[PDB]
Length: 43
Length: 105
Length: 105
Length: 249
Image 1 (cartoon, rainbow over the protein chains, first blue to last red):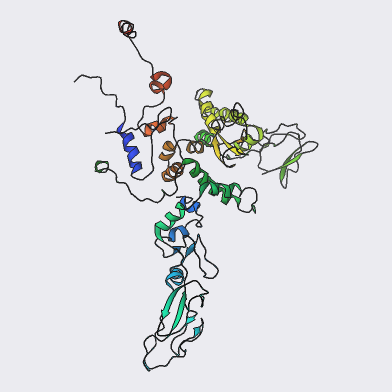
Image 2: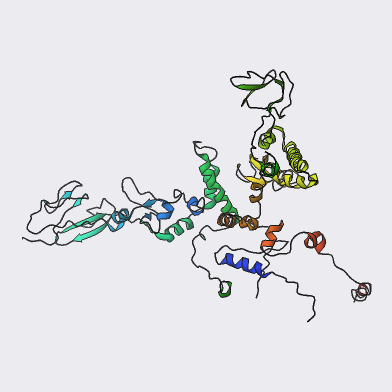
C-alpha cells in the first residue's frame, strides 16, 4: 500500500509464551504499572 | 523436582514414600487411622498392601485341607501364630477356627 | 445383644451366627486409608498453613540442634506458599488443559 | 597462569593456580628453616600466625620485615576470596580490575577500566543474611533489594530490624544465575526448577534487564526503548495552534 509498516503492538512470541505455560497449569498473569491485571489476548 | 516440592509439605520422607503412593503397592493411612499393627496406627504415614487388608477388610486366610485327613482343632478355639491347625496345614495368623464344608458328620 | 447386656470390647466388623448362636466381632477398624493421588490430594487439602508457620518459627528456639538445616529447608517452601496465595492443593490437577490445535500443528 | 585462562580465572573468581599466601593480620616477619619444611611467621605482641610454605615457594620478604594485613607474602596470585573477607569488597574490587587489565595490557590491548569496573560491580551484586527481618537467615539476596529493607525500615516505618548482611564474592557465571528474573533464569540448563520454585511463590518479574524482555519479544528497555526517552512526543507549530483553538470550548 505504501504505509509506514506496522507497529506490532503485542508480539506473537509473547502470546505463545503465556499459553504453552497455561497448558501446564501455572497461572501466568500480566500486570500494568499501578499493578492491576492487564490482558494481552482478547482475540 | 530436585528437592521434591510436594514431598516437603507433608514430610513423606523425601520420595520412595511419596513415589509408592499410586503405583508401587502401598497405601497412606490418610485421616483418623484408628488401628493397631505392631504399634498403633501411624496417621500421616504409609502402609503395605497386606496391611490395609488386615486392617479394614480383615484377614480371612483360607486353610485348605487334603481329602481323607482329619484336622486337629475343635469348633470354638482361639488358634495362635505357630500353632498347627491340621496335620497338613498351619496357622499363619492368630485366630479362631471353624468347619467350612465338612466330609464326615 | 440381650438388651443392655453383653458388651463388645473390641473395634470390629461384626458377624451374626444363628447356627452357632454366637455373635463374632472381627478385629478390623474403620480407618480411612484411601490411596492414589486423591490421598495425597486430600492430605494437602487438610493442612492449616499459618499453624505450620508457627510449628517452625517455634522450631527455631527449642530444637535438638543436630540437623536443623532440614527443618529450615521445609520453611522456605511453606512461607513461599503462605504469602503467595497458592492453595497447595493445586499441585494435583482436576482439569488438565489442552493447548490449541495450531500451536502444535 | 596468564593469557585468556587468567581472564576467566578472575571473572569466574576462583581459587587460582599458585594460591600465593597473604597475611591475615599485620605484624612482623619470622621465616624459619630453609631445609626440612619452610615457614613464614607473622607476629606482633598478641597474635602470632604461622604460614607453612611449600619450599618451592618463591616468597619475597627477607626476615624481620614489617607487614600489612592482607598483603601478599609468597608471590603469585591472590585468592580473591581470601582477599574479600580479609580486606574488603571495595578493596577486592580494585584488585580484580587492576589484575585483568594486567593481562590485556601486557599482551597489548588498550581498553577503559570503567568497562571492567561495570562487570566487577555485578560480581559483588549479592549478599548473605545475618539476623533477618522477614525471611530465613541463610538467603542470598540482591544488595539493593535489601536496601529498601535497611534504611527505610528506619526512615519512616521504623521497627523490627534494619536486616544485617555480609558481602559475597559471586563468580560472574554464578552471579549470572542468581537473578530476580525467572524469565531469564529459565533459559539456563535447569528450567523446571526455576519455573517450579518461581510459580510456588507469587514471583513477579518486572522485566528489568534485557535478556528477559527479548525472551518474550518485548521492546528492549534501553535506547529508543528506554522509559527516559520513549515517551517523547512531537508536534508542529500550526498543529499547536490547533490546540489553542480547541481546548477551551
